[PDB]
Image: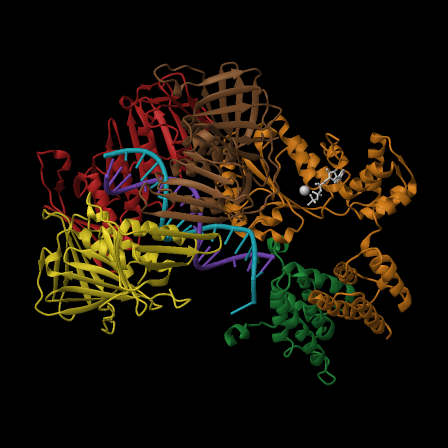
Chain colours: A green, B orange, C red, D yellow, E brown, F cyan, G purple
Amino acid sequence: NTWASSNKDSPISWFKIVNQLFRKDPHRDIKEQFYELLNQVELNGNSDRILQGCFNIFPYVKYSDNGIRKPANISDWLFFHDLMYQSMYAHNGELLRYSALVPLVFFQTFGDIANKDDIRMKNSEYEQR
Amino acid sequence: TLSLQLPWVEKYRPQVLSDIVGNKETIDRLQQIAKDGNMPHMIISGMPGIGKTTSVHCLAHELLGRSYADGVLELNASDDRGIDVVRNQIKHFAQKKLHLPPGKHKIVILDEADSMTAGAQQALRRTMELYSNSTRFAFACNQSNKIIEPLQSRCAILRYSKLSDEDVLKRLLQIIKLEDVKYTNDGLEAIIFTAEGDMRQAINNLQSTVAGHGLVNADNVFKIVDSPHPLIVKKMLLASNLEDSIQILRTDLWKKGYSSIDIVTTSFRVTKNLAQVKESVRLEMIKEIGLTHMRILEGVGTYLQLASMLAKIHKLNNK
Amino acid sequence: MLEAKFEEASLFKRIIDGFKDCVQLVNFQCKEDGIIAQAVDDSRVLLVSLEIGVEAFQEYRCDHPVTLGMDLTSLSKILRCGNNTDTLTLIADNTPDSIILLFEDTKKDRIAEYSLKLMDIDADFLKIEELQYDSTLSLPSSEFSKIVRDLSQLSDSINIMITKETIKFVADGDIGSGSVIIKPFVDMEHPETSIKLEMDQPVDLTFGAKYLLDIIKGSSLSDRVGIRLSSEAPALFQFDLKSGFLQFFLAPKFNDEE
Amino acid sequence: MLEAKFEEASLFKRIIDGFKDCVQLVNFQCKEDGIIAQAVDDSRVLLVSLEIGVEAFQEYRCDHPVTLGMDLTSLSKILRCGNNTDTLTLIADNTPDSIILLFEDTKKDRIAEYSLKLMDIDADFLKIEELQYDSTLSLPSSEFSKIVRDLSQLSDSINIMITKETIKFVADGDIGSGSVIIKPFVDMEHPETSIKLEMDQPVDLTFGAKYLLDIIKGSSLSDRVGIRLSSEAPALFQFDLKSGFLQFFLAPKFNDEE
Amino acid sequence: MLEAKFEEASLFKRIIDGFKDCVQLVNFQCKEDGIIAQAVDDSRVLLVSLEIGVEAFQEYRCDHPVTLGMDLTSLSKILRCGNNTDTLTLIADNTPDSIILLFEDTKKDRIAEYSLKLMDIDADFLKIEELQYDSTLSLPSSEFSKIVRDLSQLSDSINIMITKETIKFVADGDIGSGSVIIKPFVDMEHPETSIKLEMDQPVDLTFGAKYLLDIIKGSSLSDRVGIRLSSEAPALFQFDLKSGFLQFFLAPKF
DNA sequence: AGCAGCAACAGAGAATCT
DNA sequence: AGATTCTCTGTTGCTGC
Ligand SMILES: Nc1ncnc2c1ncn2[C@@H]1O[C@H](COP(=O)(O)OP(=O)(O)OP(O)(O)=S)[C@@H](O)[C@H]1O
Ligand SMILES: [Mg+2]
């Protein structure tokens, strides 16, 4: 069991951040959890990989479902992220600050107390590419 | 004119650890370290202008005495700090023989450690590990996350925080007493308000106001050093009626020469860091502030786009 | 203390040229009978060992041995001030933090003096030389350099094979194979061109071409090179000096070992 | 079979230096009257054509022509073992998978032998040389090299213009323009420095400077260079050998064509 | 107009070799008493100043001064056609858009002619040379080059210190420190090897090694180099030509 | 789907030594 | 005068932002 030095100097594996984005703690303020997650997503600098992780995980996550609209609202964000990511190669990277907001929409929409188990993930996109 | 005088930030730069009005805990820690010796590897992180470089400089000076010239190796971001430099010069300095007191060690100060490349940072690990009995490393950075975890594992971590109102007020009062300047309470209050925990910026604004008007008054400070940019943006976004926000944007920001890019970007920051409203409405406001940004980055940056962004934010806040 | 004056700075410069590139740290030790120096590369397949007797110097004084380690690169950087004809004096106290190199021209005129920072290296000189080697051979060093330079182009491994009255160097790689075969012979018209060979047992060893290339540099110190091979130990390539020698011990490749 | 022995490995090395860089694959063919070789660059604007008669060799035997293709780079990599004074023998059977280069010193001593892997190339030798060219001129090759080296700096195109008793090389680009004008002349004090010109029709062609730069290498094979130009075909730059020649045919730029 | 013919293209090529690398733009001006040229590097710590009198040329004609600026890199690119022994003629009209370099061999044979595009530079020649310097010294330029080449390896700063009858060059950096001490002396066996020194006041200045390295190039123009130092101004390193000189003024490190 | 900053490797030119 | 070695410059590739 070695992890103390990691907590001391290492960040949050993007996978751990994805599993944390689908978890809500019932004992903490939702706003404090949101700012803690925002800081973790910003410190990682790899918002794209976190979002791709969220995209692969969301169909397998338990989320109180009314008509699966939550997925429809998230397709519009994901489309907003793809436009932003295309614009990063055309324009000086001022737009990079908004990239951390798209992963946090998953915490708002799909974050549930039911999601206690870590879902492992893979990279279907590199294989598909 | 023939020559200039030294600025008050450099002239009154602290040379002893007692003159630092920063974080008391870390300051007393470094003072006791310099008193006893055995300085370990350290990484000091924080925000610009809070006493990080001055702190490590004072520590090295007090710890080395007269041997500061031949026992301290200073490397800033202005010098090459790549893999070749770490391989040759840093290793030659760490391997250099030097007769020091039985409580001191050679210090390698690396300013702006968050800018060193990954190769140099990786090579520095064994460099600081094999010569940890005659050479010590002190990093000074603004983002501790930019330094690799193996390097952080071999050193202490000192996180410097913002300077409270009392500390900056005390330092400014000391500077005024040492300089015999005419001031007033509201002027110092406005200076500290425009400083935002930045001691260097506070002293710079004080010196500029003194050299421009002579009397440190809130009117002079506000006419020379415009009010904080983020506060007017926050007051504009937190407006309850559309006409008030529009008038604020027109008079305070647009009629004073603030570019639309600065307005929208400052706007994004204010929102991200907002705490008055809920999370969902904040995310919707950030979303709207984004479309206006995309349109302004495409060259469509005008007052109409910001007005439409404010209208959409108010419509979101309109339940 | 260290006090060694070379007649010509050139000799020391060529000696250091030999350690150059293939090693980073060198450990020198001066004593009553001269100066020795050893350097081992990072992979530990090559040892460079020097010995300069008292007679190689114009002036040498030692009443107290001194051991000093230094970065080879730093030393060579400073080793191009000798004008070759300049006089060079190495100087150091009994507990040095530096080594002083003093170059002076005959007349009082120009004096270039350097103070090189030393490195602390755990004193641990190796004594890996053998009593007898399977085979021993010497030949002109320029010839050995050509042989190495030829074959090097073909492979990263050059094999040396010795049988009665036959020495054969071989390289075999992608573009093909090559070989250089030489035979022992005494040239009275000038014996510095002869090729001697004493074989007690046939040998067949492989060396990493990159290392043999480092070794050939010794040609600049001696007309001939001695090569001693054994199946029990690193091979020895030796370049004699007037009162001294520069030796390179190279471990044979096991199958993949430089 | 192929069996060609060059007196000096140097001649072959300089010949290959000519194909070097500007072409990747070369197709050789030995036969009863000698050896020929052709190589065309990828863009097909340059053809390098060689002919070495039987008399250029110290020993040549051919009872059965052999065609063999190879990578130029691989060949040159191996072509620095000739010591220049070494003897070189090219050897190959009638259905080769390789070409053997055998370098030997006068005495039995060093024998460097290479076995180069061959490439299969569809035999298709071109015969694009013309009966008559619009204009013909020869001048010292070192002079031609200087002319090319001058102008090259100014543009990627160098124009050659010929009128009665006048040869003019011109380059014009960003930094400005340059020109070198030479006139025919017979120097009896040594005719290898003369500049001959036979013009049947004025010519004016443009060539890509990068190619002329490849061509000037032939200076190392001959004192003079012959240049034959036509508005109907690639220009011919020729470097004579003792019994043989190295020829470079270069297509003029159409407006943009090397 | 500009009409200056050099006997040997080599002289001009070596002169330009001196401006080479350390400066990008050079401003030439021909006039009745010769040609002058000035170039300042971007950081403004080095000024390269040339003067070639009428007598240095085989033929010189000037009835109307012409000032012309150009990119040195472009100039040197063209300055390797002189065969050294070729004759070189610089030519330009009174309101030039270009400068013509004409290289010709003795015989009518080969004529290489270039037309270099000019740059417009605000004419502003500096006149920073001093009446008296604290100290003045001359020594063989090859010796000065060696001194600079030695020390350069040790540091980016080389200090020159002068006291009565003593000149000392010093460098001190990471690997250690070095120094070269020379003393004034008259060699009658050939005075071009002597080392003269006239000291009115001891001096001690530091210069950036990268710049001294640029300056040593002048060795190719003269056997000796004159060095004039002052605590009040840029140091002057001078290489004399037959009728002329190439000067390098270098600001000491603060 | 630029740039840049980089760093490393290869080639060419110049200088020194035999 | 020729050959070899070393140094400098340019180009290409890889990594990071
Ligand atoms: N605690 C302090 N007490 C007194 N003066 C201070 C203090 N902190 C900063 N200053 C002043 O600010 C100047 C600059 O401080 P620095 O230590 O360079 O700032 P910093 O905290 O290192 O942030 P950087 O350098 O932008 S990353 C000093 O020379 C002082 O004049
Ligand atoms: Mg700082």
Q: Position of residue D11 (x, y in %)?
A: 19, 53
> As displayed, is residue E18 above or below residue C153?
above
Q: Nearer the viewer, residue B31 or C158?
A: C158
Question: Can residue A117 be seen by looking at this rendering?
Answer: no
What is the quadrant of residue B139 in the picture?
Answer: top right
Q: Nearer the viewer, residue A129 or C252?
A: A129
Left or right of E215? Residue E126 is right
Task: For ligand 1, give the image quadrant.
Answer: top right
Q: Position of residue A48 (x, y in %)?
A: 62, 67
What is the quadrant of residue C196 in the picture?
Answer: top left
Left or right of C236? Residue B233 is right
Q: Nearer the viewer, residue B287 or D22?
A: D22
Q: Nearer the viewer, residue G11 or E96?
A: E96
Question: Can residue B138 be seen by looking at this rendering?
Answer: yes
Q: Position of residue D116 (x, y in %)?
A: 22, 62
Q: Position of residue B145 (x, y in %)?
A: 63, 54
Q: Which image quarter is the N terminus of chain C in?
A: top left
> As displayed, is residue C243 above or below residue E31?
above
Left or right of E27? Residue B178 is right
The tally of labels here is 0
> As displayed, is residue E146 above or below residue F13?
above
